[PDB]
Structures are given as structure tokens and as C-alpha cells.
Amino acid sequence: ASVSTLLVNLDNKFDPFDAMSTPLYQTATFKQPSAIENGPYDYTRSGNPTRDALESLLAKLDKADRAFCFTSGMAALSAVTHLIKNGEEIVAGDDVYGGSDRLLSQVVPRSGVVVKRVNTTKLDEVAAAIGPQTKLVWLESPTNPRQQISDIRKISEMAHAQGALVLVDNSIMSPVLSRPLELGADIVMHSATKFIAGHSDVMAGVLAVKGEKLAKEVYFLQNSEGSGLAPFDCWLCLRGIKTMALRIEKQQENARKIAMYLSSHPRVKKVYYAGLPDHPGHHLHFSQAKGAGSVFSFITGSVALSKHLVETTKYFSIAVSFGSVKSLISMPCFMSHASIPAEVREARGLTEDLVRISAGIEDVDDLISDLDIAFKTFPL
Amino acid sequence: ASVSTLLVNLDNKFDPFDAMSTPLYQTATFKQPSAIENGPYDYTRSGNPTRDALESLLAKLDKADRAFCFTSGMAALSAVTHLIKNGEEIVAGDDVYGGSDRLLSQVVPRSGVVVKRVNTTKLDEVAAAIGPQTKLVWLESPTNPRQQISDIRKISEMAHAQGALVLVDNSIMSPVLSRPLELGADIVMHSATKFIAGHSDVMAGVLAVKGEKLAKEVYFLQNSEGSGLAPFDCWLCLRGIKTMALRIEKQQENARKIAMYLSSHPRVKKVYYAGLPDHPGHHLHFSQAKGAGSVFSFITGSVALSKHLVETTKYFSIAVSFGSVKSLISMPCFMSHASIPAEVREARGLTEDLVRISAGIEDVDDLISDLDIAFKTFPL
Amino acid sequence: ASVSTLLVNLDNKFDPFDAMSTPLYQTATFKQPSAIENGPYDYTRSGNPTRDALESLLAKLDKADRAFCFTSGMAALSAVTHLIKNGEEIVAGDDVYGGSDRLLSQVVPRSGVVVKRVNTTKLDEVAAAIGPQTKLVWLESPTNPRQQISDIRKISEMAHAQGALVLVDNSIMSPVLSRPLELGADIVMHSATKFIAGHSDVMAGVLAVKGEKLAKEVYFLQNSEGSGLAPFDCWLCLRGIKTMALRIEKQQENARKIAMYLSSHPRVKKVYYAGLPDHPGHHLHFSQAKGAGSVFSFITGSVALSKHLVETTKYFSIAVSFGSVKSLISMPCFMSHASIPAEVREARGLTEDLVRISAGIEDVDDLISDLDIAFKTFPL
Amino acid sequence: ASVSTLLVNLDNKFDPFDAMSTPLYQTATFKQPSAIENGPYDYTRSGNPTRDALESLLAKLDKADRAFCFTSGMAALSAVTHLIKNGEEIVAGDDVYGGSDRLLSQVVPRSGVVVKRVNTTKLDEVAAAIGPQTKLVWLESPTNPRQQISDIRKISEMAHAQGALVLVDNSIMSPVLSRPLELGADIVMHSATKFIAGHSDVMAGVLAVKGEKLAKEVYFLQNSEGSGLAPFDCWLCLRGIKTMALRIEKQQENARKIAMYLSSHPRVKKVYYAGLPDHPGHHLHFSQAKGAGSVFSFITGSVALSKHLVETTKYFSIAVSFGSVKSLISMPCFMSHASIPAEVREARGLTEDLVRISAGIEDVDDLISDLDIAFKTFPL
Ligand SMILES: *Cc1c(COP(=O)(O)O)cnc(C)c1O
Ligand SMILES: *Cc1c(COP(=O)(O)O)cnc(C)c1O
Ligand SMILES: *Cc1c(COP(=O)(O)O)cnc(C)c1O
Ligand SMILES: *Cc1c(COP(=O)(O)O)cnc(C)c1O
């Protein structure tokens, strides 16, 4: 039974009328059966039929013991973070996403937790980083925007060697291309704001958990810090996940073709994309994933040319994130860090002229044609 | 300019078409204007027009500098909590609500933050408990379900003279009966799931802040822990908050009358309601609140008769919380702590037969008659 | 069992989890149980659980056999209209609302259905106009904006003695002030866009029917012309209808007081409101309605002063319709028929300076003070 | 600029914040600028920014002068029908859809309009059917479930020859495969409940019009009979139309492969599908369309085998309609007419054992495998 076939099934047992869409329980409380006993549901912060339908499809998708839905990706990562106590340590790949950065830096500390940074690509570096009191190993792969690959099976054994939990933020791959729990991770997180919902109209975060005692501790925090995804947002996620395989299938192929057109373009200096045969990490990646994705970036050594591509293209929207049906284009180097000086950007592997693209589901000839016209209009 | 009157004010400067209802911005991202600069908005976790319209109304209602909306009441209490660093001190009443209790005993510790519990009605204790390390004082008055009154002006001065922040969870009072920031509090919090939304159909928390620095610090956390209330939810709060003054007016009056009836009823031992002249705290409370709200409880000395009133009443629903248009009834001891033993149930100031009622907006003659019959049908 | 009390009753037999809010069935199709038989539901155009929950409440409020919800007020009036065959006769007041007017003069004719217009306050005319071909009598009392009262018990007997159906568009009264099916009417219609939903945010029409055959005939049309109100809309009506009794109570009282003030004001020539003792029809209306509602108008003999009151009032919005929590003000002559000439504007019983107000639920001292200032700032 | 690329573009001029998703104007009224003049919007029944964004994308998709959105497909067809006056005629292909049937039969008549039926495949039949006073020619192609083809260019000239309007109900093809306005039709109707929204969670109907005076007459009825699609439903339509090209592309290909597997299956007697080279009409169809679609049917001469396939398959849902991401299966012969006797089904070209499939976007091997197992389990 394929993913494609699994994403559209409606297994809503509770529904007496078998509607084709999951009924939306937009309520806060439920009436109890008696003065002494509760019902299956009582308060939405604790549990809700609609969110249960989504959390449950997502556990199957990730082959997890239990899945949890949060108001956003950051909320999911913040909860994970509230699992390490005072005097513990966290080995954080130092490449990891902006909000993840800010979190590991400015927030995790106020809690008496220690934060180690590394290059999860160098096993020795991460080997030396895994201390006695190391309780969490937190990875991302491909990284962004460079697409550098890390070995999740091995980093899993080093960490598991100290009795530590491995968190794999799979947002960039989604359950259709990768399933980290089957590579040794303990918790896979997905910003569902990206591929899962795929329409850039809903914030959501997902924690997919391996191990019951573990899941019980996540539920404790989803239910106590009250960050469970709202019923309406769950419904929009349920509606969107249905075409996830269909959308990734077209998107990724658009990305392959635009990466190839750019790869051999006179004005493009380098192209990062794990799908290119020439990508350092290519073979490593595909040993743990079925696809490169639909996000990639490139350099042009010319910041004035890069701004032009970004601002001139008619089919790409200038925006953050990726994974929507609309193709996006940006400069993470002078934008996704506008507060980044000349040393603030150099202190972060990236270069003022770097352009990142999130390919959508348009006709790739429309997109390649759009980019070509854009290079041919830049004056000198 | 009265509150009833302020609540229906539609202040949407952004909307070109002057809709009578605030346009719902159900979107996760916004397009940036150029490659270098951002727009007023960029990402719903960071900010959204619909949520801004609500956070603004809420700041005006509470006379706060800025207000913040969180995915739920607990999320809001959880952020205030992430303001206090490793090894600092938190002094919080003993009465403090269930979820707050749990958060105070099992999550705050994980940060090395120390928690002292006090009976905030006894100034000495408050005095005794507030040292050099105290950075947060956390009140709640009336207490649930006894409706104990604490002096908020005097507790604020003590803490401030110690440089501590004062939080008042004003959920049971809401903006139209009390505005704690004018009594020394620094942050007022509401479970907007209760009176603000008013229909039992949306989960939401609000944080009303005094002080630009503080606010900046609350915003920093609402944004990084990605917990701002979602747009559909903000829209439902905006919609339900409009009848807030109206709902409370009829509700409060209903509770008054129903306490009247129970107070002089032969099978009712004690009635807890701050509106009753005979209630310890009456004059204190009304010295800092324009009214006694709509939740109250009573004891009957008979766990068997209490269950009976609870299950037999035809017009009250057996449910958790309050502040909704529907009248609710429950038993905080044998229910809102159901899995509670003999001393583990009395380990909380509440005899297991205490019944709590949340008056709604129905005909009070229907509700009072509903209770009378239930008292008469009880088997001996 | 009072109306205020009936409005919050949650009667959802179908829902397994007893949510406090009716589950929204946002779906177009339902799965059938076998290849041969259907289920309770199959297609939202045919029926939906959420819409059923509302159509049921509405039948109980109006003491009707069955009720139907349409995409809007006009859709409902348009269906009643599709009940009358080729070459039959329709007798409908002259006063009858704009959209109804248009529908009566430009669409009903296309069917060979003949339309006679009468001043339903003059029984003779009604008598004179009702022949052997009359199959529908269409009333509206009070009339807009003059608030003319027609005798609904006596008009029903005449038509019935001629075998004609009687429709009463009860939009301005709603179920808590009048229930026309207990006065001889056969179908009562409401623009649920007005008092029922009560927040200016949903378009909806309701048809409350007396008689199984008739109902069957209305259902046949709601179903075939695919016009039943959509599920999200039904849910918003269910949500807003709960404060209906509460909203009207404060609203009606507000209108009373504001008519009081204007009636004895030096710059106001005539005030039209059926609650005023001096109003022709007072005793008739209150002989068939429990109240005068919240819409009324006044003349000032000065088109220039009327525009001024309309544009200067700070607390009234310039807008069409009524029944919302927000106070509205407008000029039916120079606005709700703006593109109206000199005799084409007087070709409707309304002097071009008539101002209509719809009282909302704000502080009446705020509203009355708002009007006073506007009378005082008017340039001479 | 391809359709695929056009379906995801956001051309919302009015939006000051450029959200990626169209802002939802869930309101009924808008405030007017002054006492004498309206704004662009005033009442949702008349016009709404969100519906305008959808009606406008749909005009581009169909190459129409203006597009209109209705509460449902039937509402769209019912409005079309209110365009022919008393004493006019309608030439209705007699094969046309159920609700279309019911309408042409039981409703259109009460209006003094004459109804002719034909086999739009026989030009002579339709030649003889086009009278002097014929104002509407109403087609469907492929028909359902037979997929019989009609020539839309020629039937367009015969009709236009009498000054008549041609209505083409394109629901089964959608704008991605066919655009009838470019073949002589005047109005193309789409049940948007099908392919446009594609998630079976929203009812909607669409009229795409050629000719301004024409469009003005449709707007008159959408605006007067109040059947304009609700803002929320428009938003769900906007969200769904975005993957329409992506969904039809996979769906149609699944259909091709399942039609081919069934075509050569021992237990299948006939397969109707315009994409099969062997289909009477094949070449005719593709002269006016780019694809066969994803709906087809087949016969097995065995009603007991057909029920079994329908009720045994694990990946097909038993439901009406088509065009959703979920594959559907049914027997229109003994189900989509359960009230169809032994002569009531014979009086309608179809046969008790006929099975219709609407292919979804699953893995076609999952679906073919599911059907094969189903044939191999039927006992004798
Ligand atoms: C986009 C992104 C996030 C942010 O998630 P939100 O849902 O918007 O808070 C987290 N992690 C990664 C790896 C991302 O790339
Ligand atoms: C209900 C309640 C809360 C919890 O708020 P949620 O919206 O349910 O997370 C917090 N404080 C008080 C005093 C409450 O009564
Ligand atoms: C407003 C109004 C209508 C129209 O209803 P819609 O919901 O706007 O279509 C019908 N009747 C009366 C008497 C009205 O005042
Ligand atoms: C499905 C169908 C319709 C029905 O439309 P609704 O939107 O559900 O009312 C109309 N026409 C055709 C041709 C169809 O096949």
C-alpha cells in the first residue's frame, strides 16, 4: 500500500455519517457522561477528534509510535527542547535553521542546559562533541541552503551510545522522501507549514515519536504548555496532506530540471542540489532518502545580478520558506538575515549573492524561461 | 467611551473595503517587496493582521502597553514562565489553577527556577516568602472554587520593592470587571477560552503587558516558541468578544440570583460567591473589581446529593471551565481531580461534595426551577 | 422552557463526543454503506448534519413543522416564489423590501405569474386585490422604514378563504418578538443575515413552514435549485443565534431610549417607531408581537442635516441592513435607492431626508451623546 | 503562460500585505464612505473581494468575458434556466445529468417555458428540434456514464442560427481539458464541487460567460435570487483550484491505465472511455478537448458481480460524483436511481450491472491490484 494511496484514505471511525472530509470539531469543551467520569474527550487542549485524525495519519507516514501536532514548527522544536533538564547537554548541528539557531542560543540556556555546536558532517567533530551528560543530538539534512549531507545512521549510534535522543528535523524532505525513525532517530520534526500543508496558508509543527515512554513525555508538554495545533489548522493540514505525494513528485522534478539548466549556465558559478550527480554527498543522501527535494540554491559571485534575478522574475515570489505549490525565490544571504553585516554573514557559511529557489508545481518551461529572460536583461 | 461600546468598535486601518468584519488572513507567508527589504508582515508566527486587530483591542481593554495572543491560556502562562532564568525564584499562591499547578511543580523546576507556594490571602506569608531572588509573584483572585480574595495592590508593592514582576491571571474576571494593570500588576493573563471568546468553541490565551522592555521580552518568546494564537482562532475571538460585556451582564446577574436561592436553601450548607454580602472578602474584592462574576460553588455535605444535582439538572451541562453562554455544573473534587484519593482529595481546600456552577445567559427562572426540582427528586 | 434558554440548548444526537459546539461537516459527499442503499446523508446539497442542527432549532423557535436554510434571505424569498406556477396570482404589499420589490417586478413575471401590489394596511384593498387566482399573499410588518402595522390575523383568513398561501417576511422581528405561524401565516421568512446571525458576518435566509405537503414542496426546491445555506455558514448562524435573545433585549431597549430622545428633540420633525405610544399601529402591533424591535427612523425636514447626522456620528456606521451588534445609520432615500431622481425618489413613501438607525448593543449614553453633538455641530 | 502556471498565481491587487493566500472577507456588509455614495463593496450578496478573486481566475481559465460563482452546480444551472421567458423553448440533450433532468422536467415548466429533448449526437434530431422560438441549446459531452460525444461547434451554429444561446456543462472535463466558449458555446457551467475544488468538501457552481449583455443578465440573477457562492466556500475553491492541473494530470492517466486493464479483462463485457482508441467518438472528442478525463464505466452483464466489485474493493469509496483526489466507484444503474424499477432503468440508457469509476490520485497499481483481487474473489 503506497504513500500516494495512504494520503487520501479516510479512516474516521468515530463518524456516524462517513463524510468524505473529516468533520471539524471546532469546540473547546465536551460534555462529560457523569459527575464522576470523563468521556474520551473533555478539553481541546488535551485532545480533539480532528487533531487525532491528523496526528494519527502522520504516525503512519513516519512509521512512528505516536505523532503530535503543534501550533507551529518552532513550537514543536521548543517542546523537544523542554525535555533536556538542568545540567544536561545538547549537541546541535551548527548549520541548523534560523529559529532553531535563536532557540539553541538565546532560549535553551536560561534553563541550565548546555549547548554544543558542530558540523554533523564531520563524525570526529560530533564524536568529540558527544559528552557524558549529552541527552540530545539534533540534526538537519540536507542542510540549508548548502544541502550538505550528514550520516543519520552513524550519528544515531554515537548518540545512542551515551543514552541520548536523536532529533531529526525532516521538514525539507517530508515523509515521502525520508523516514529518519528507520535510521536510528528517536524524534523526527516537520514544520508542517511547508510540504505537509503545501499551500502556505497554515502554520503547524509535527513531532513523530519512536518509543512509548518518550511519546508520553511529549504528550505531557503538548498538553501542559498548551501548544496543540488548533482544530481548523488540523483540518487544513488534513486537506493539504492529501496531495503531498502528488505535489512533491512534480516539484522535485521541476527542481531537477532547473538545477540542471542553471548548472550549465554561463553566469552561474555553483549549484547546490543533492540530486545533481556531482553533489558532494549525493550517494550518501540517497542511501537514506528517495529524493533530492525541490529546494536548491546557487551562487553568481554577483550580488547585483542575484537581486535582479530575485526581483525580476515574474513566476517566482520573493518569500521565505519552501514547499508550497508556488515557486519561491530569495537571497538568504542578504535577506533571511537582513541584520547580517559584512562579518555577520561571513560568520555564517553563505555569501551575499546566494539565491535560493523553492520550485513549485508550475510548467517548468515557464519557470526556466522566466529565469533565462532574467539573466538576459541584466545590464552592465 | 464605555466598554460595551468599545467592544464593537471596528478599528481596521489596513482594510481597503471597510468590511464590518475583520478580514481573516489565513496565510502562513507574505510576499516581500524586494530582495533586500521585508514588508509589514512576512510570517504568521511573527505577526498577522487578524491577530494584530485582536491583540490591539485587548491592550485597549486592559490599559496595557501591548497584548499578545497565544494558542491557549496555558501557552500564555508558559511564556510568562520562560521569562524567569536558571536558578531564580517564583512565588505563586497555593490556590492557583490546576494546569498552572502542574506547570509550577513539574515544568518550571526543569529550568533550575525555584518555586515557593503561598496562601496569598495572608500578607505575612507573602512577605515571608518574598526574598532577594524573587523575580515573579503569581496571583489569582477570586480563587477557585472558594472565591478567596487577595489584596492585589499590596502584593504588587511588596514584590516591586523587591524588583519582582507581578502576574495576575484574571481569567475569571475578564476586562470588564477588573483591570489589574491599574493595581500594580505587570502582566495580566486571561484564558480567552473562557469569557472573551464566550462560546466554548475556541482555545486561546492572552497576555496583557505593562512596560516596553517587558513587552519586547514577551514578544520575543511568543515569536521564538511559535505560539501566537492562529488567525481563524483570532477571528473567532474577535467575533465572540463583541458580546462580552452583554454576556457578562446577564451572566453575573444570573449568578447573583442563583446564589441568592441556594444561600437560603435547606439542603445547602455553605455558598461561595463573592457577591454575597456575607462572603469574606466582599469589600476587598469590590475595592478592586467592579463585580463578582458568574462562577460560584456550594457545599451540601452530601457527595451523593451533589452528584445528583450535577447529573439530574436538565439545563446545566456537566463540563469543565466557565464563562460560556451555556450554564455548566460540576464537582471540582470528584471530577476536576477525579483520580483523587481520600487525603489526596482533601489535600486541596475542597470537600469532595463541592459543586461549582457557571451561570450562562438563559432565563434564570428556568435555571432556578431546574435546581429546585433536582433537590426534590433526590432519594433518601 | 424560555427562548433565551432554548437558544443555548445543544441538541446533537448524532455526535459521539458531545462537543459543546456542533461539529461542522465541511464536506460535499458522504460514503454510501453498500452498492444498493444510501446513508442518512449523501450530498450536502441534499442535506448536511450541521445545517440540520440549525434548521431544527429554527423550526422549534418558529413553531413550524420544518424549517429550511438558504444561501441568503433573497434565495429564500426566491424559492417561496418558485412555488407559484405559470399564470397564477401573487398579492404582495407595496411597502415590501427592495430586493423583494425587484424580484416581484422583474423575475416573477418571467414565469407568467401575475403580481398585484397593495397597501396591506387597508383591508379593503387587500380584499379588493384577492381573487380566485391568488395563490400567495406576501406581507411585511412593520414596513420599512415607516414601521406601518398590518393586521396579519385578518389577512390570513381572507387569503385562506381563497385558498392562498400566506408568507410573512419576519426579518425585522425575528423569532423572539413575533411567531407569525401562530397568526395564520403559512411560511415565515427571515433574512438570517440580520438578527439571527447578528454579527454582520454571514449571509443566510430561513424559511419556516407550516404543513407537511408545503414543506415537502419547499424542500423539493431547496434541493433542486441547490440553494441550502452552506455548512460553515450554518455553523456561524448556530454560533451567533445563541446570543439572539440577549442581543435583542439590550438592542430593543436601546432603540426605545434613542427614539425617546429624538421624539422630543427640536430639530426632529417626526419619529417612526412602533414602540412609541403615539405611533399609529402601536396597539395593533403589540397585539401580534411581543416588542417593537430595534430599527426606526426619523425625518428632520433637512436633507442637509440628515446627511450630517449620518456622516458625523462617531458611533454609528454608515451601512445597509440592521440587526447587528453594531449601530448603523443611513438614509434609505438618498442611499438605499441613491440613484433616485426627484419624483422617482418620492415615488416611494419616504422623503429624501429620512434617516434610519439600527441600535446595537453599546452604551446608550454613548450613542445618545454621539447624536447630540452631531445636532450641535451642524452648520447654518 | 501555461494553465499549470496560471492556477497558482496570486493577483490580489487589493491586498496591502500581499499574503500568499487570498484574505477571506467573511462579512455581510461593508461600511459606505458617505451618506450619498457606496464603496466598491456594500453587501456580500452583491459582491465580495474573495469571490471576485475566484470568479476572476475562472474567467481567465475559460477565456470568458466574466465568470460567476454559485452556491452549487444546480444553482448555476437553475439560474441559467431563468433566462428563458414564458413561451420560449429549450432544447435539452436527453442524457443530461440527474439534477439537470429533474430541473428540465419538474421545474422549468411551471414557468411557461417549453422543453424539447434529444440526442445531441444525431445532428438531424437536434436539427429538427431547433424551432423558431428556441432560445437555449443545453449540452453535455462526454455524456455520463456512456461518454457519448456531441459536436459542439456544429450544434453551436445550428442554435446560433435561430439566435439561441448554447450552454455547455463542462463539469466532466474542467477548463484544463476543454474550453467550450472557443467552440461556439455562450455559457459553460462547471459543478465546482468536482474537479475545481477536487477534495469533495465544498459545493459550488460556476457560470463562465461570453458576451457582456449576457453576463449582465447572469449577474442580475446571481445578485437578485441571491445565490452567490459564500466567501468561505470561495476560499476553499481558490485553495483547491491551485492543484487542478496537477490532479487532473495524474487522475486522467490512472483512468487510462485502469480502462486498459479492464478493457482486456475476461469478466468485463464493455468499457466506456473516450480515451480508448476504440471509442465511438474518440477522434471527435479530441478535436475539441485535450483529454478523456478520469471518469469511465463498464459493464459485466452480472449485477451480482458488479455489486461485489463496488462493495468489495478496498481503495474505492462508494459515493456519487467524481473529480476528487479519492477514487470513487458506484452503480449509477441500480443506485444513482434507487427509485428506478425494471422499466424506469430501461427507460434510461444504462443497465442494472453498469459500474462507474472516478479515478483518484493513488498509485494505479494499488487500484488495479485492488480491482483484480475483487474479480478473483467473486464465488459462483
Ligand atoms: C521552515 C523551518 C522551521 C520553522 O517552522 P515554523 O513551522 O514556521 O515555526 C523549522 N525547521 C526547519 C528545518 C525549517 O527549515
Ligand atoms: C481555564 C483556566 C486556565 C487554562 O487556560 P487554557 O485556555 O484552557 O489553556 C488558566 N487559568 C485559569 C485561572 C483557568 O481557570
Ligand atoms: C435585508 C432584507 C432581505 C434580504 O435578505 P438577504 O439576506 O440580504 O438576501 C429580505 N427581507 C427583508 C424584509 C430585509 O430587510
Ligand atoms: C455533478 C454534476 C452537476 C451537479 O452539481 P452540484 O454542484 O452538486 O449541484 C451538474 N452537472 C453535471 C454535468 C454533473 O455531472
Image: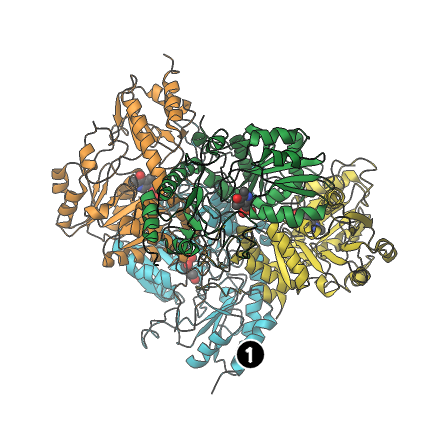
Chain colours: A green, B yellow, C cyan, D orange
Which one is in front, D74 or C377?
Answer: C377
Q: Evaluate whether residue B249 shows in this view.
A: yes
Residue C107, position as x, y percentages in the image: 29, 57
- Badge 1 density bin: few <14, some 14–19, many ≥20, Cα 10 Å: some
Instruction: Specify whether D122 is left or right of B5.
Output: left
Looking at the image, residue B312 lies above or below residue C362: above
Residue extending furthest toward the bottom: C380
Residue B295, position as x, y percentages in the image: 71, 52
Name the amino acid, label 1: Asp
- State the image quarter where residue B122 is shown: bottom right
Residue C227, position as x, y percentages in the image: 38, 48
**Residue drawn at x 34%, y 58% as measured from the top left:** A379
**Residue drawn at x 66%, y 49% as measured from the top left:** A107
Q: Evaluate whether residue A204 shows in this view.
A: no
Q: Quadrant of the N terminus of chain A?
A: top left
- State the image quarter where residue C148 is shown: bottom left
Looking at the image, residue D350 lies above or below residue B281: above
Which one is in front, C147 or A174?
Answer: A174
Mark 1 C-beta closer than 8 Å to ligand 3: no
Which one is in front, C161 or D75?
Answer: D75
Looking at the image, residue B234 lies above or below residue A157: below
Q: Secondary structure at mark 1?
A: helix
Q: Which residue in the structure is indicated by mark 1?
A: C372
